[PDB]
Amino acid sequence: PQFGVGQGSGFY
Amino acid sequence: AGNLNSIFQRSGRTDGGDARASEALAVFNKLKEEAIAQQDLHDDFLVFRFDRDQNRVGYSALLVVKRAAINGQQVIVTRPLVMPNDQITLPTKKLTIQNGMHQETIEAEADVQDVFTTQYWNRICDSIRQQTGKHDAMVINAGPTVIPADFDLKDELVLKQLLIKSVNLCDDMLAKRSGEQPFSVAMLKGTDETLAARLNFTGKPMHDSLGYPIRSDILVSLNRVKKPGQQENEFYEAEDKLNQVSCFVNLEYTPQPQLPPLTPAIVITDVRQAEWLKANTMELYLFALSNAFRVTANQSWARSLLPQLGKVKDMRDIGAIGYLSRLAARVETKTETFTDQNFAELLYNMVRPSPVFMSDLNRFGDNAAIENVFIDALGGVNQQRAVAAIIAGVNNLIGGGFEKFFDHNTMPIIQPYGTDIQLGYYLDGEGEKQDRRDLDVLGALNASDGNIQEWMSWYGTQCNVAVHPELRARQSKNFDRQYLGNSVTYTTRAHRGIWNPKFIEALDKAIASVGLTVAMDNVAQ
Amino acid sequence: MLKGTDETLAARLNFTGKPMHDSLGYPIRSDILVSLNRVKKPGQQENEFYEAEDKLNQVSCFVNLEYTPQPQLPPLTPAIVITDVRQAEWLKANTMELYLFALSNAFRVTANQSWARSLLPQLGKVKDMRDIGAIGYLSRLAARVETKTETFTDQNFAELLYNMVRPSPVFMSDLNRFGDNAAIENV
Amino acid sequence: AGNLNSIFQRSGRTDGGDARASEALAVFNKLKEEAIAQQDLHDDFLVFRFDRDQNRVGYSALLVVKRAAINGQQVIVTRPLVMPNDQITLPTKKLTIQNGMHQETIEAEADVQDVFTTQYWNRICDSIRQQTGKHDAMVINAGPTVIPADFDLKDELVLKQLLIKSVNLCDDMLAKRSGEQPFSVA
């Protein structure tokens, strides 16, 4: 139902 | 207590690290050196061990690390390689499920999705700084992946290739942070060059960076842009390929309040550039995705559903479709009286004419640095940023104008499919690895041999997402033991989503509209 | 740095019948291992992301007996002898402050009469050396006390201590110029 | 592919290519080190790889390289060692011959003289420059040679001598470029 977000990088 | 790490780590070194992270470091350092000796790898970088003992993770990992200073900022790009250890159990998480008025808790092991928390990453970054000396560095996430406990560590070839691929990606991300120029149709659009493409009805699986099989019914091959009459590049031999997309088509049994009952669910399972190209960027990815669209837009995917006539062991034989149809029976497809015309009729009555395009999304896959933007684009705190990155990537391909087809803020690029994906493989009668996804709708109908009640119990498990996913995962595993066999190994899980039809319209039309014409090789069926 | 608002300490006295080993694998005698742990309130903890342990430090003590005849007091005066001082394996540093904090673990081994458990008999041993029944040779009995058998009671044990062992031990320690703590022990 | 390779070869590396060429690079590296240890050769030269999957080559080669700055010009001197492989098929020339009144075609595999074209040389120039970092250097062709497909790589003596001789030829060409005084009857 919800979207968790990990520590992505470069694009943001 | 956890704040005593500020004292614990102030000075000195210790004797520690798990047996797999120890062995993994030793083989990876060996491989680095051989790659340098053979001149395949450049000697500009470091490999590091991240310990569960020395620092704050549940699972140890090796870190593929490269660095450069970019416009005064120290930048490090890291691609973690998780090392699960079969002898080490991390305390489980409590999954409390509110089943209406009944509350029950299931305890379960943390998978790489649960392990790779935001703090897990932040701890990886801190350890690297301790190991590189770059205490003020910024660290780029190239996407964690995992090298599973199960197999023997002696496969130097694969391990070498993992380092090679991981450093490739690290160089890309330093470059793209450095402002490197994007992939575009303009680079392909020679004034004397054109594209062409075909659908491969493979009869075989394709394999990820660790050698595990990936389901594909159709491999779409986009030919190298070129033209007869161009200057030949000396005495050369090459495959005329630019890129490819791996996909499969299921037949989902879907609701209706006149359409037939099954949906042609076209699923992308992998996106690859031709092997001669080294870089992996969003523009390259996005351009290749148009390969799946053409599967149903210009050509007809339904050929992939033909039964393997003459082969007794076809677990996904189309004849099974008769169990969901009004026949409530397997269609006799073993017989000399079964024709192409009869096949088409089964589909006329059972399968909807309008294709649906969706894809897997895997934060831990071979393309994780990129998969992550497409995943965050599904929803969450940074959806707007992920979407902005994706639309920018297509505009880089076409020179602007994606926005002339649709509003990305009214039409988010990828929607959730809800039911997520359990990945794994099973062994066949000769011991080969096959994708567990084979028990799809036709697969499951043959597995139960027409027992529709058994099929529907399974089918509801794979569709009703009001049911907590742990409950669904347990029943999915129960069904594999009964129908697939006990020789089943589970691998890293993944998300699925639906590509917005307007994203698709804009990508395909925008490329065609700027003149990068592609011919179909299968000019007529 | 230890006084967390969500953190307290607690300790356990271990009476197990096994030795410790030093830095080159040689045995160390002790009767009691005093283990001091970090206990946190069950809210958010750093360990939500990792396997974790609460050991802070440990002091290993031996319980001795000094014979002090009076030509009255029970003839044997016990002592708590520190045979080793260690920090938890999590802490790489070894300093004076850490050593001193850990020493408070020996002090607490004498809470109540816990330290005297080291003087008990233990299971099934036909002829073995730390048997309290040997104490009967210095006491009026001039004989070994039948302590290893099914006819020896808890009450008889308590009586051997009441008459032969003084209830309050002397604290002392062994300082090794060449041990791993030598930088500190030499002070 | 060439329009893309400009930038998408810059980021990342791969494995692959002819195993015989990899063996040849490895035996030369071994011999190089033995020669340094025994003081037969100075550790002042580099050996690079020229390979199929990167350069679309026809035949693979090892490249022996020396460098000097001569009157301000950075100069790279090299001697390629071409490596044919009996297990690898090479594309042929289609030779149309007017045999009297009728044209017939004979196909033949390109030989080392057909493969080592001016452009092959230009790609050697560029490949070495990228591996040495001297992107604006002038490159001297010291005269290539060949290590034929047919035979055991077990003749370390021959391979050692080829390396020594290649190094010497490279030095003579730099010496010419720098104005070294000629041999004369004087």
Image: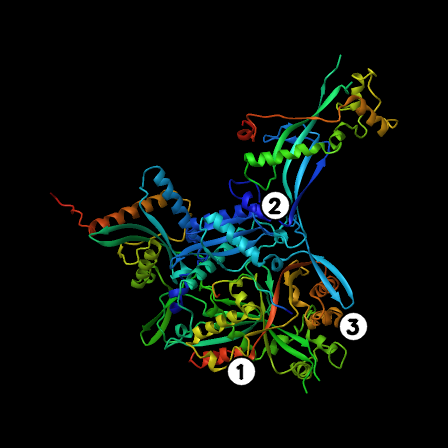
The Cα–Cα distance between marks 2 and 1, rounded to whole angstroms, is 79 Å
Q: Which mark is residue B524?
A: 1
Residue type, label 1: Ala
Name the residue nearer the viewer: B98 or B60. Answer: B98
Q: How many marks?
A: 3
Label 2, on which residue?
C3
Question: Chain letter of disc 1?
Answer: B
* Residue D172 appears left or right of B302: left
Query: Residue C49: x and y, percent?
Result: 61, 53
Q: Is residue B210 visible?
A: no
* Residue B263 appears left or right of C112: left
Q: Tell me whether the residue at label 3 lies in contact with that at label 2, contact meaning CB atoms closer than 8 angstroms.
A: no
Tell me, what colour scheme is on the image?
A: rainbow
Query: Residue C29: x and y, percent?
Result: 67, 27
Q: Is residue D80 visible?
A: yes
The Cα–Cα distance between marks 1 and 3, rounded to whole angstroms, is 41 Å
